[PDB]
Image (cartoon, rainbow, N blue to C red; front, side, top):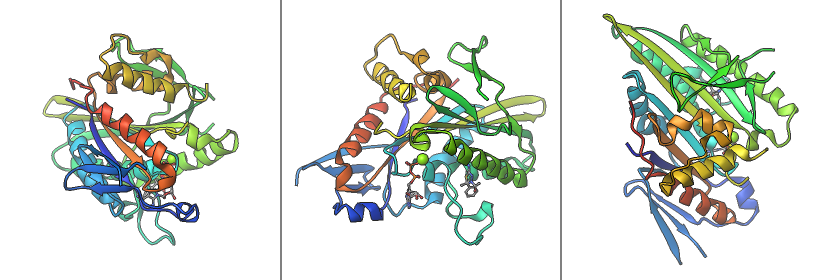
Amino acid sequence: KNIQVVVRCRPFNLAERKASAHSIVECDPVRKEVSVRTGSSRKTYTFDMVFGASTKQIDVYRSVVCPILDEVIMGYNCTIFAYGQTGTGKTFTMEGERSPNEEYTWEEDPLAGIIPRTLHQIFEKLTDNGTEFSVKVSLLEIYNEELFDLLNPSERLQMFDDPRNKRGVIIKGLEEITVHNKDEVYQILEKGAAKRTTAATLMNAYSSRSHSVFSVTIHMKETELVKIGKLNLVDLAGSENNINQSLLTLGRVITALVERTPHVPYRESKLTRILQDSLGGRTRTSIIATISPASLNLEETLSTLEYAHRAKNILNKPE
Ligand SMILES: Nc1ncnc2c1ncn2[C@@H]1O[C@H](COP(=O)(O)OP(=O)(O)O)[C@@H](O)[C@H]1O
Ligand SMILES: CC(=O)/N=C1/NN(C(C)=O)[C@](C)(c2ccccc2)S1
Ligand SMILES: [Mg+2]
């Protein structure tokens, strides 16, 4: 199956209003098109889905992620990437935010993004639909070609080949935490958030240059036939950017794949080793390309759109 590629455009922000920018992006969800005025000259792209600035978190989840979670629960591996310019909505999309003033429970918060909703829906979907299951999660960051375990309450992780799968790696020392119930989900996410703000203190431009890999693995057993599904939820460093080796190598890998070049340089960065199987392997993969509507960003926005559109022709073969 081909990589699914969707675009999410966010509303104008006030920094763009202060820069005197005008709108140059038109999202057409019905036609699945994004049009960019390139000076009345225009460039249109077609994607698998297009989400405009009024799209709600829950819309993204139902339209993009629900199909993918169903595949995981069938026992496949899946990956969703968020790709795009700093400030355009990668983290808002993958993680979301809490609404102000303690107004919602985490499970009901309309600003939750893909990660919290996915973990909540795992428990809704598998609970007492006949199923015995366990769920574990891990969260690592990649910064400056170094691995950081956001769930380790203490360091630096070591990468080993997976002798069982050539397109795979094993991260020794990664905290893979069992999530026993919905209430545990929020405690674990809270714990990763605290670990990331202190990650913020000891880093240079850390969040915009770091990659974040959240992984959930579901062990499922029914009578006695077993299923193991994995989902990786990846928030990439900003696309405008050892500090950039992984982002740059991701660009070479995608290029190598789109040109059918026989040498794909997967092993030239930690990110591309981790998601080697997501890029031309046996994992089903979607990319959410995030963009700004503002004229200020024409060059980054065109770069993001070209990058993402080319990705549509990469074929994966799940299982
Ligand atoms: N679709 C959207 N609607 C409203 N606010 C958004 C949207 N996307 C991003 N934002 C806000 O814009 C700011 C930057 O988004 P963020 O997701 O942190 O960007 P990135 O991770 O790409 O740098 C944040 O305050 C975020 O809440
Ligand atoms: C890796 C990741 O996604 N981490 C998260 N931490 N959150 C905390 C601590 O509120 C997020 C923002 C959230 C938002 C709404 C509902 C529940 C969780 S998501
Ligand atoms: Mg971010």
